[PDB]
Amino acid sequence: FRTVTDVDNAVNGLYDLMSGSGYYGAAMFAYGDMKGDDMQSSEESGVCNTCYMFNHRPNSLNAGSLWGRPFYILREAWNILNAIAEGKIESGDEKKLNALKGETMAVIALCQFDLTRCFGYPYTKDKGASLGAPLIDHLVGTYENPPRSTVAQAYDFIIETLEEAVTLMSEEKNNGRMNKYAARALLARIYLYHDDNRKAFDLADQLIKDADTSGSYALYPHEKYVAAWSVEAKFGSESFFEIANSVDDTPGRDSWGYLLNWYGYQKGFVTQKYAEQMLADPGDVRGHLLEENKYAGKTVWWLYKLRGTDLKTAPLECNNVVLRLSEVYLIAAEAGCKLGGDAAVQGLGYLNEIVKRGNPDNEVTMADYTLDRVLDERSKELVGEGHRFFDLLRNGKTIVRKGGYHLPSVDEEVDWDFYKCVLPIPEDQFIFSPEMEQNPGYPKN
Ligand code: NA
């Protein structure tokens, strides 16, 4: 760590780590989609299957690297911050160093947030009273083993970190990494998850306004929506942050794009419920991402959202979207609905923008502007993007996963009282911290 260039390279390495199939290369999406009601596993083995079946245990999480990889990134990220804070970097390029510091803090906030929503019960269950993951809110000592902190403690840190990050970061685009827009989009999400509905609405609203005034981001039009999901259209106008993948880099056959593809590893489908939701409205362009085929003597539909240049060749090089503009519209819509008043009027406007982009013949009237209606819009819009499980559970909903072509023994009702709505703490944590608590319900050998 001698120069600002060294710092830029270190920060770049954080995203290299994040792109692994164990985290944002695949596992995060398997986790968010396969645990909802809109996607399911096929008979194939792997992370889609174990997530769908909530087949997780302390000696085998069966959830990619959703513990190890974010923790590893947090350690490397804090090494960067510490170098900067200790005065290790040469002078002269200070504005950029500050941008890199902010960006590093944004990475830390994302990693800790993911750990919190994977290993702690939803904040909204209990005002964050349950235990989250260990909280990497500092440079960890050589022989220090941080304890578990509460979900509330993690949110306090995550929000403060990201609020500060935003003030330091550049608005310039850097494809494959977060910029100030990405960081604000993530913060609006986190405010929403934290029940800070006014903060979520006000931020989401201003971010949309700023995208419009600058022209720097824009919603895909109805007629261009399917093409916007192509490998030929990377870093599109909605994308604040996506993981950069290529044909020559890992992940290839274990990238989310290859796992979901019928012609790739065929790990999952949309559910009959999602397919029926969409095909009842053929004018909605989001249904054009579904592809019909035949599995175990039934019609099924798979999700062709990570689109290569050839229908019948599964792609190795698809980028995974992490933060895009449509989510921000839905955050404003959800928070506005929860707030009522003027925020509701405005949030309905944003909801309709997404509804009508999907199908211009549709609308949502004020009489129909309910939380369930906004969550149904999220279902439609964000399938395959890792949201559904979290969006239902944080709103205290029961996820119903029954009938259709669901697999035998699927958990048919999942809510925030289900002990496997969080992953277990890995058994090897108890080597150095034997008195650390395991999540309730799980065994402790
Ligand atoms: Na690849």
Image: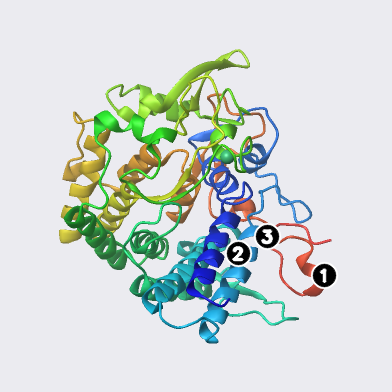
Label 3: how many Cα within 10 Å (few below 14, some 14–19, many 20+): some
The crowding category of the residue bearing disc 2, from other C-alpha atoms within 10 Å (few below 14, some 14 to 19, many at least 20), is many
> In the rendering, at what x and y percent does residue 336 appear?
25, 57
What kind of residue is marked 3?
Answer: Gly
Give the number of the mark in front: 1 or 2.
2
Tell me which numbered mark, 1 or 2, is placed earlier along the sequence.
2
Point out residue 399 in the picture as x, y percentages from the top left corner. Answer: 50, 43
Q: Amino acid at mark 1?
A: Ile
Image coords of residue 14 (percent x, y): 56, 61
In the picture of the structure, the residue carrying the numbered disc 1 is: 431
- List x then y, in percent, for residue 310: 48, 22
Label 2 element class: helix
Q: Visible in this render: residue 407?
A: yes
Give me the residue at 53% from left, 24% from top.
404
> Pointer 1 and pointer 2: residues touching (CB < 8 Å)?
no
> Where is 328 relative to 430, above or below?
above
Which residue sits at x=34%, y=45%? 372
Q: Residue at position x 35%, y 35% from top?
A: 228
Position of residue 20 in the picture relative to residue 363 (left or right): right
- Residue assigned mark 3: 68
Q: Which mark is residue 73?
A: 2
Quadrant containing the N terminus is bottom right
Residue type highlighted by circle 2: Ile
Foreground residue, 270 or 266? 266
Tag 3's secondary structure?
Answer: helix
